[PDB]
Length: 50
Length: 49
Length: 49
Image 1: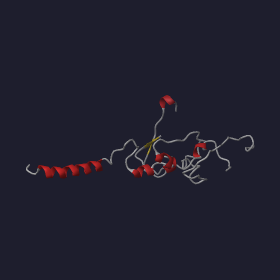
Image 2 (image 1 turned 180 degrees about the vertical axis):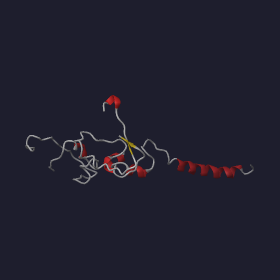
Image 3 (image 1 turned 180 degrees about the horizontal axis):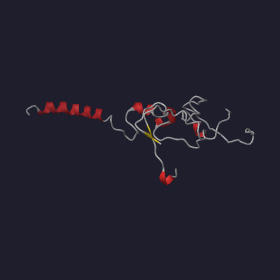
């Protein structure tokens, strides 16, 4: 979607693994504020949005 | 309140320790107050500061 | 020390800094001292196919 109508999708109630994301997209920038990605594979969250 | 002085000594000390324990909850600017999360959700380079 | 790496990982080459390049691939100590150098080289190491 375009910026002025960004799209939001709720993802919950599932086992999330953030190790598969390295695949898709050369990923010019992948950075986090408040967590560090190598440790991101461990914690449990409230409600993650995309 | 005939024994005001002795009772007051006890309360001053108890209150000092109590506030010292309560002050552990303050964050002082860190992203969280308990050490476990900081060491859990962050890499060592940022966890230092 | 010499080797060849990707173009989105330069930040990853640091003491104990997270990405996927400095945890299990090859890692430097947490007290590192020195300098790091990287240069994208696509004119001598990348062929057609």
